[PDB]
Length: 90
Image (cartoon, rainbow, N blue to C red):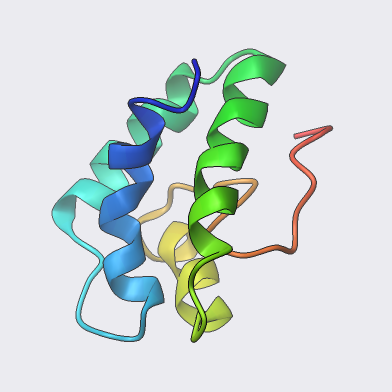
């Protein structure tokens, strides 16, 4: 998992994190799917790198929405479009 499919999976959730209407009916199904499939540390560490490289370029990144993605639908992710996680022991 060299951050190739995970990107498009969390990409739909960014639409909300930016501070606009979203995320999308794909953010919950899309991210819950990857999350569910992520049964190894590898899939948790790889995915974290995806959002990290991305979020790093978001100047007006919003934590309120980024953190409101999982509690909304009920995906519960151990990381979002923010730099407040380790993804080491998740």
